[PDB]
Length: 37
Image (tube, rainbow, N blue to C red):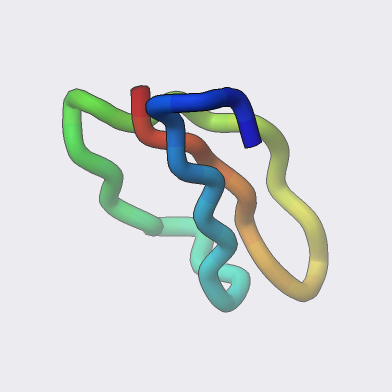
């Protein structure tokens, strides 16, 4: 994880709601990956 950033994964949720400070990385069948910047 790049310094100052935080990568977070959550249980798969097609309707996942992320903050404006988040960027989407990818969506899996098990979990969804995003990072805070």
